[PDB]
Length: 254
Length: 254
Ligand SMILES: Nc1ncnc2c1ncn2[C@@H]1O[C@H](CO)[C@@H](O)[C@H]1O
Ligand SMILES: Nc1ncnc2c1ncn2[C@@H]1O[C@H](CO)[C@@H](O)[C@H]1O
Ligand SMILES: [Mg+2]
Ligand SMILES: [Mg+2]
Image 1 (cartoon, helix red, strand yellow):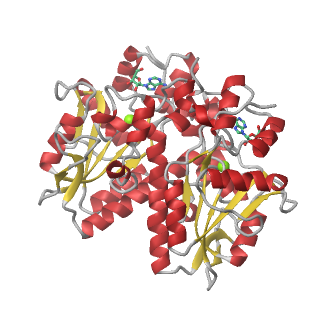
Image 2 (image 1 turned 120 degrees about the vertical axis):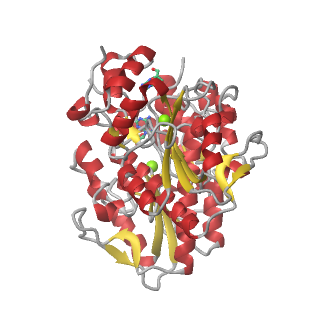
Image 3 (image 1 turned 45 degrees about the horizontal axis):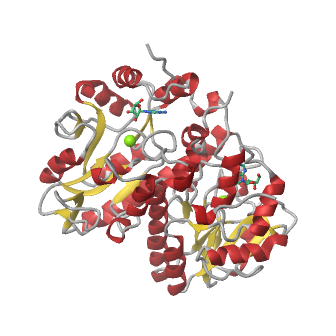
């Protein structure tokens, strides 16, 4: 009779709201500093850079911008996750497609996303969305973004979707398009693929966690790359016992 | 054969490590500014202040300090949560007591906690732990803190535990003791009771979430009060369907 713990946490708890507000406060402070003192590097990795040796698209004289993942980064998909909890069928690509098409009035903003987006625009920073919602559902997604109070997104200018190129769920191509036009000074997401495709398509659960602590990646967290919680679905909900609970740290009760 | 999703997320995922590193980066930047420009208010609520109208213990000329919850804020209780996942018996106060006594070699630091604590001490900020581990298990808890790389804690100076007063799991009394001696300029936690007992002992799930968005509270997140994720146990894992999925945001698949 109770929803899954991850959904209780993410959608129900004050803990999760405080955590999200924290991310957006750190992001606004970071953008503010960069608006006063424009950086040499943008926050989007250069083509061909690896997690071994991160290099970035330079900032240049391009217009300042912030890039956001949509789902569980600025918008909470309450309707869909209600359905998943009611039915137990969270993995259902056809129902997800229906949801992309008809869910625009069952979303809520992530706590602080509305204030955060308004502030970015008042600082002269363009807000750009890069989501793996499908291109053919661009218009319902625009209306869902507007309904969540996040403003007016425009396909191919400030909204980039899966299928806008032939890389599928890989977002690096769209990041490159975006970084070719703007100086992206902050990027927000709830999954590591919202920052680099290099975290996915191969690396194990333990490899990906280690990669976030690589020094040139680790410096980005809360300082260019901003993270929102998602213990409900996606690339964080993987791994067996040996990858979640490493064996030097195990213990048995008496 | 797979652990609970919240544990996959928190202990296994790079998503969760990046999120924690973000919290500690924002905290170090905030402490740094406060070390240059000492504030008038500390970060600990004054006695008698309400969530309606937050007021704070002044900073004065007291020594600078940062206060941390221990469990799932600076230290990951991997051994205990392995046991909980293996057995299904997460709520077991006797096994938790055993764990307090014998788990010191089955803990890991939260990503970034070791670097963060070292930096605070190099900046001249005293690191103070306020945990609801029990007073009578102070010494194993000191050794677990040291094992996690978090340095040397001292009962009644830099380590405060449940039972140090007669308020039980209520931490406001110990916060007051701490704020009477230090200018606490940052406080970290994974549950709202790590910031104020006023979030607990009454308020419903939806009330507590709303309270984090009260303006004078909302300004603290990532800016004095720093949050770490815990979708595994505690006050974030509460509420029925109506409190997790509000009814204006519900949706049915076709
Ligand atoms: N609870 C969930 N479980 C699985 N996939 C989910 C869930 N919520 C949303 N999704 C999304 O639904 C699609 C597959 O069901 C993917 O895009 C995935 O990200
Ligand atoms: N998975 C868990 N479920 C319930 N309580 C837990 C869990 N992990 C740790 N605890 C702690 O164990 C004690 C009760 O089992 C409480 O202090 C609670 O915070
Ligand atoms: Mg997302
Ligand atoms: Mg804790």
